[PDB]
Image (tube, coloured by chain):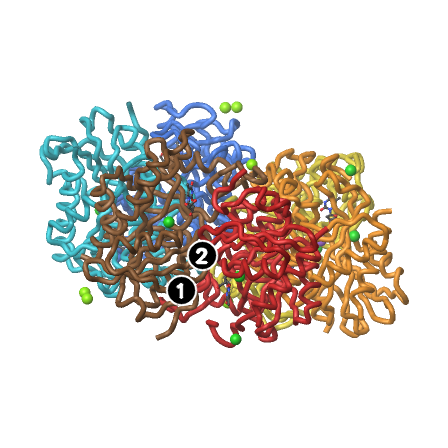
Chain colours: A brown, B red, C cyan, D orange, E blue, F yellow
């Protein structure tokens, strides 16, 4: 009966939803919801915009997370309090491998925990791993969209800048831990950087929740060509089509 | 002349070198309107950005979202655009029985229960505010008539297990955080929030001046889950006034 | 042309690029004989090596011994000899009440309670299998009629304190591991073994494809002493499964 | 009721709740004589203890020896005897080019390159001074006419490799500390000393007020191997005066 | 009365309280036959176990396999069966230019580059031998005419990256271990092997006496390919030495 | 040069390459006077420095103060002046019931509960004595007639919480140290002091020879007060022992 503190929704508001799609950007919430039936705005507070919709007759929540594990952890927790058990993350990513192209899609098979919030759920030795059904559904949905799909490891960083070894910054400095790190992850086969998967996957895998992450590649750190506008727009649309279809696969 | 997330240019800031950085995008306009000629600049994601004038000087107000990661983006991008001083305001849960709802806390150092701070400095580095900003915040807070506590803040990457909340879906907390609230209480830590460790470490190690003031809206010795906010933002604007040179 | 420990050459492998890597040297022949033309290659230390053919393709079977360190040597040396895909089968103790003796587990990620994984990637790197291998193992395991669990495996450098066993010489468990079985249980961890963290981390960070499948021999919430016929049936099914998983991985 | 190391009783302190804690036992009498009625109490090991009176109030002066471990014993045992406020004075090497020999530094937070701080709080906890003490030290240092810097201090369990000195027997520095001076410099750290991390962490986590002020006697951008000390103790006594009320 | 892996019972050990624990199963019989009435007890996995008699006292010889994890099992199960003293002999690669191939090393402490030691004691605990065992080993080593070095051994969960070997499948060494051989050299570390940290930490924290002696088979500052006659001489001497160290311990 | 803290020159040491390093400045003269021609060299801060002659050879006696940090300065500066061997003597609290006040402990390895050791070697590195110094100290200690224990010492940067003392101002002990005394006791640790981890790690990683010997004057497990005579005898015996250990180290 309670209204969760941050998301401002009740369990009844979710109309029985046990699955949530959790993009990063609040603006993307409506966009995902309208790919389903009967999208209804529930609430917007802070970075959390929440809609409900229906997919093959089943209630689905779409809720933005904001950037980063901390804000993601709140949304996932409060949704879980309200009965959500499956969380499908969709979000943009920078690829770091030359073979991954802008417009491709990555389904994370495990995340490098370059975050802090994951540690609030499990010690570092615990794997930031998706639920296998979710990863499988995301792969299938991504392939069916016509996308080129990569399964692999994602580096999930609490920062956009030094943790992704960006030097074009105010200080131009990167702390010792992250100096040379992009090359190290590249050499280790890591596909991409984003900022939420380690927290999400660790939290869920250690809490009896099913989670997975799919991402559209919007830049490649190894390509000094500017991503074409059309490809990006197409990638935006494809990513959310894919996550909704992955949700469909998870429901039945 | 652009930044990746904030959607504003250096020109948009009209020479501002100080930012007030609340967490909640909805607080941005409220803070801006406490100043002169507030102007909406941009809103994208958790980042709503206004400018206003305070004693004739441009000040930026920019929300951070919850947590170190989104905060770190805002601070970096504001710094790219010339901002050098960052005044954090927000709400907080006190963990000391003598710190009351409505009191204000000015953080003298943060327990780094975050990940992003480590992306700027190793854990041994202190998450401490710039002394002038802390001084200005204490003065603004005290001058307002508030009851003000200076001290250590536990700054957590989570709202729930890292602040040892149990009224949660799993109802459990990982080993590291079991008993942690009592430990911080024993150690004299005043309060929990989610951004100061990142902000203070990032800034103290990057030649930026930062500080945090917080309004206490719950006492965790009383209960787990929750006018103070209005008073806090008046205080931070006065702190900004004191920082203006 | 030579490796330091395995005592086999690239030529001995006859072009094999896939290895099945059980823990027990005695299991190697058993696995090899599920395939065509099994040939004993070498046995040195804990490394017994056979080759066989699966649908006309050479497959190597090589034991790892117990633990990440000896596993890491075998994987490295096999990789030097051209092996790129590693299918681990091994016995395991389940820790979840709902995971029954005789069930099978395919590891989706390992809790890195080992040291050797850190020699390949820092702790934040996930000990996760190659998705194709995990998919092949799940399919093989399910097709066999087994009850199959996908999930997290706690992978320990010890059998005793790191798996929170107290019935030991000292009866002591270091602080780090006191209460750890309950913690992993609460976190949904399915089982304990002693090699997957090393194997999965090493491979995932080295451009090698790896996965682990295991037959549940005991459940820690029940008894430590397995029933002989049950164990035998589980072990036989597990090696049939890993061979079919290899079949699925063949190109 | 005589503490294990310091060789004094609570009665010996005549109600003092403030201590000045230099490192060198020889400085103890020198600080004490800046106050009224200095009396020698005890000398054992590196711990020389005097009492004196400052504006009518009893103050203890107690040396710490070099390093967190010996400092921790002195602070603990003084605290057992009623001391609640600890003012550290000492010498320091600056690592910033703009900080000059003769300048003073008031530590706003310490990089915890020590071990004893961890015996009081985990590394995440900030080695930060009490704000009142830091404020009093700044004011006292300024009023002496000293050039004063507020900022972060790297506090090392060694004088040599932990301060990245190479003119040593081995001439080498362990991986952790190779390039560390430059890293701290880049992060805006002002100086190196050896006690503040322990002192500040211990006190901040134990309900004790502490701060550190230091006279710069060498600039490490200039050389490795090293009036400043006279003025420094004047300043710390004046900071003590400000703390009393 | 039984154990989980070694396949021997307390009765099988005939009251032995001392074990010689080589790494290689094939070395077990070679050690046992230097004593009286050697008898094969069991061979399961990497664990080959013999008993013999030394000056009228039963001694067990039990291989460990490679690595701390398999070693920890052997030590634990032997301790369950009454063994209290563990003498490790094994081959090693020296990293100091002044330590020659054919020299012997008695470990005075190990750099804990392993994971299993942490399952017995946190990292700050010293991986230290029992002083009587180290003393006996030094004496035995010296009496054999060997050139003997007492000092620190780096004990790695891997043979390859943890010993900073680059001539590998990936040719990569994780950041932690890049430059590590030079660091250990500069710190006076004598040699690398893969079990002593686990063994010494486990034993020193569990009321068991342990020590490690090793013959230098290669020097990393020289060549990786040992000369056969030199290697054979060194290995023969090492097992003679460890049996004499056992004699000294049992006196 | 005159070293910065110790205030002595190389010439002042008259060729000494061995130092006895007690903690307490007041103990320096007492040790020096057990030898021939004791000469006061300097006193600054916690560093009182004497020279004396032992069998015609110059020996330095230099106090360290309490704790690794001040110890590290003294060892470094003496090493700059040619000192290569460092014999630590002091008193200690035992934590094992079988260790009696008046017994002596020679440290075979230290639990690194300090910070300064990390400034010389990472935590994995063992805080272990030079074998010759430990051997000499054991011999000197046993020849004195004392009961001598060889074993692990817990070396703490604090006297209070790091030794799990609760009779303190806050009565609080941080999580890391709660239950730690029982843990070290169960791991066979003999005693607590506050310098050995730093000293041993520093020296063992820097090509310096060091060891520690200590007289037991308190036992944390015994609720009886040791009498004056015993304590006096123990203090005197400890320094007689360290000087005899120095004699044994002279070349
Ligand atoms: C392009 C890119 C996006 N992201 C994530 C961060 C934000 O959440 C979002 C937009 O930048 O996508 C990265 O983390 N790294 C990248 O290189
Ligand atoms: C009331 C309260 C707020 N906060 C902070 C974190 C977020 O920035 C914001 C909303 O929860 O306030 C806490 O961290 N803990 C609390 O108990
Ligand atoms: C039954 C069982 C096996 N194992 C693994 C370890 C060895 O690799 C092998 C033999 O015990 O199986 C465990 O790790 N835990 C268990 O509970
Ligand atoms: C000059 C100087 C002093 N100190 C401090 C530590 C001791 O407390 C004291 C003696 O060196 O002064 C440093 O740590 N570094 C320095 O460079
Ligand atoms: C020669 C050599 C052996 N060893 C150990 C590992 C194995 O246990 C055994 C065989 O290689 O000896 C090393 O660890 N490093 C070496 O350089
Ligand atoms: C009695 C005792 C002494 N010590 C050491 C610390 C000092 O160096 C010296 C005096 O207390 O002896 C301990 O560390 N613990 C003890 O229990
Ligand atoms: Cl998004
Ligand atoms: Cl806010
Ligand atoms: Cl409340
Ligand atoms: Cl097996
Ligand atoms: Cl001083
Ligand atoms: Cl200078
Ligand atoms: Cl061997
Ligand atoms: Cl002493
Ligand atoms: Mg660098
Ligand atoms: Mg618990
Ligand atoms: Mg059941
Ligand atoms: Mg069942
Ligand atoms: Mg030579
Ligand atoms: Mg030679
Ligand atoms: Mg506790
Ligand atoms: Na956010
Ligand atoms: Na001292
Ligand atoms: Na093995």
Q: Residues within 10 Å of mark 2 (few under 14, many from 20)?
A: many
**Residue D40 vertical placement versus F12 (above, below):** below
Res C29 → quadrant: top left
> B205 or D212, which lies in front?
B205
Q: The N terminus of chain A is located in which quarter? A: bottom left
Helix, strand or loop for disc 2: helix
Which residue has dot 2 on it?
A70
Q: Which residue: 11% across, 53% down? A: C145
Q: Residues within 10 Å of mark 1 (few under 14, many from 20)?
A: many
Residue C185 visible in the displayed image: yes
Is the Cβ of the residue at disc 1 closer than 8 Å to that at disc 2? no
Q: Which residue: 44% across, 41% down? A: E155
Residue E77 percent coordinates (x, y): 32, 54
Report the label total. 2
> F28 or E59, which lies in front?
F28
Residue E208 visible in the displayed image: no
Q: Quadrant of ligand 17?
A: bottom left
Residue B109 percent coordinates (x, y): 62, 58
Which residue has dot 1 on it?
A7
Helix, strand or loop for disc 1: loop
Tell me which chain the residue with mark 1 is part of: A
Q: Which residue: 68% across, 63% down? A: B140
Question: CB of residue at label 2: within 8 Å of ligand 22?
Answer: yes
* Tag of residue B156: none
> F166 or C111, which lies in front?
C111
Q: Point out the frontmost of discs 1 and 2.
A: 1
Tell me which chain the residue with mark 2 is part of: A
Residue F60 percent coordinates (x, y): 74, 43
């Amino acid at each position: 009966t309670k209204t969760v503190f941050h998301l401002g929704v009740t369990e009844a508001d979710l109309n029985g939803a046990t699955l949530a799609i959790i993009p990063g950007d609040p603006a993307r919430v409506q966009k995902i919801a309208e790919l389903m039936d009967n999208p209804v705005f529930l609430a917007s507070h802070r970075e959390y915009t929440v809609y409900r919709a229906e997919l093959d007759g089943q209630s689905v929540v779409v809720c933005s997370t904001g950037i980063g594990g901390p804000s993601t952890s709140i949304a996932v927790e409060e949704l879980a309090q309200l009965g959500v058990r499956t969380f499908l993350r969709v979000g943009t990513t920078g690829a770091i491998q030359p073979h991954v192209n802008v417009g491709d899609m990555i389904v994370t098979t495990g995340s490098v925990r370059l975050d802090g919030a994951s540690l609030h759920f499990a010690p570092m030795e615990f794997p930031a791993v998706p639920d296998f059904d979710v990863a499988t559904a995301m792969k299938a949905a991504a392939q069916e969209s016509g996308a080129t799909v990569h399964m692999g490891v994602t580096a999930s960083s609490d920062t956009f800048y030094p943790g992704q070894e960006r030097y074009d910054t105010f200080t131009g400095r990167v702390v010792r831990r992250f100096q040379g790190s992009m090359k190290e992850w590249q050499d280790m086969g890591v596909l991409n950087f984003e900022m939420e998967s380690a927290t999400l996957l660790t939290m869920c895998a250690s809490s009896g929740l099913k989670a997975g992450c799919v991402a559209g590649v919007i830049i490649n750190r190894t390509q000094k060509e500017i991503p074409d506008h059309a490809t990006l727009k197409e990638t935006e649309a494809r990513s959310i089509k894919v996550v909704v279809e992955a949700a469909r696969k998870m429901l039945k």
